Image (cartoon, helix red, strand yellow):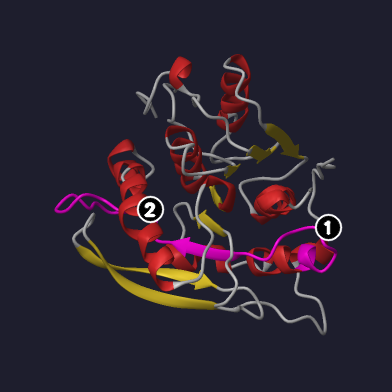
Amino acid sequence: KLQISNTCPDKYRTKQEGVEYPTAKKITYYSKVTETERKMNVILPVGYDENKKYPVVYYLHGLMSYEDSMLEDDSTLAIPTNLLKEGRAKEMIIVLPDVYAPKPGTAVTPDFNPEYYKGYDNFINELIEVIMPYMEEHYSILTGRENTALCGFSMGARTSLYIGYMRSDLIGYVGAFAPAPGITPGEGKHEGLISEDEFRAEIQPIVSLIDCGTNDSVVGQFPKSYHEILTRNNQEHIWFEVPGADHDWNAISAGFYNFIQTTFGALN
């Protein structure tokens, strides 16, 4: 079945000569959840045909530079196309949200702190009440958990795990690349979104995947702790480490490379 690569080969995370890659279009929309105008990038597949329907991956940034964050390295645009060429991924639509979606009147400046993190926690409502309906009503998409993936980096990865397990009925594929502390209680001090024994779902993700560099200076051993908790709870998932990598694009690209090989039935 799947052969997990601890490191992403350069050929897949970089744009190859003579290959066409998809492009991002920035969408401005209104959110009834934040009561503000917001933005997201939508990346349609090459040769997008409105007479076909496509599965969707939502890819969540961490504390970086909002919806453009995951375009800073070419792995996001390159990996799905490069796999597709070898028959190793499905055609898909990629959405890059602005994940910081605080309730009205509660926005604070970015801080590695639970108060700022509340706006990431609220993204569950932005995704389900605003962005998913936006995508269904503006693009030719396949709906349902078998056609819906959610992945992210750092605070975006914590948020992907949280939404992926709390709403596994909507999300079939969950990818967490170096997830941040605080889904569960841990030591600043995180009181936890949920208890360790609560970190599970009544319906399993089709694929759940977590990676981390072995030298991550920002989230440390918290991804491994999530691996350990999910194991204790028999929530099957893929866990792997990226040798020598820090909180960086080597860890992210290895995560996205392995994740996209699994999404939407690509392994058959």
Judged by its main secondary structure, the magenta piece is: loop
Q: Nearer the viewer, residue 116 or 162?
A: 162
Instruction: Please state which amino acid type lies under the numbered disc 2.
Output: Leu
What residue occupies the far bottom of the structure in this picture? Answer: 18
- Quadrant position of residue 245: top right
- Quadrant position of residue 17: bottom right
Q: Is residue 145 above or below residue 78?
A: above
Q: Nearer the viewer, residue 133 or 62?
A: 133
Tags 2 and 1 touching, CB below 8 Å: no
Q: Is residue 35 left or right of residue 185?
A: left
Name the residue rendered at 45%, 36% in the picture.
162
Binning the other alpha carbons within 10 Å of mark 1 as few (below 14), some (14 to 19) or many (20 upward) gives: few
Q: Position of residue 199 (x, y in %)?
A: 48, 23
Q: Position of residue 234 (x, y in %)?
A: 62, 18
What secondary structure is marked by label 2? helix
Tell me the magenta residue range: 82-109
**Which residue matches tag 1?**
9
| Image quadrant occupied by the N terminus | top right
Q: Closer to the camera: disc 2 or disc 1?
A: 2
Check if residue 102 falls in the magenta segment.
yes
Check if residue 3 falls in the magenta segment.
no
Q: Nearer the viewer, residue 34 or 111?
A: 34
**Which residue matches tag 2?**
127
Q: Is residue 4 above or below residue 149?
A: above
Q: Earlier in the sequence, mark 2 or mark 1?
A: 1
What secondary structure is marked by label 1? loop
Q: Is residue 212 left or right of residue 14?
A: left
Name the residue rendered at 75%, 74% in the picture.
15
Q: Position of residue 241 (x, y in %)?
A: 73, 37
Residue 255 visible somewhere in the drawing: no
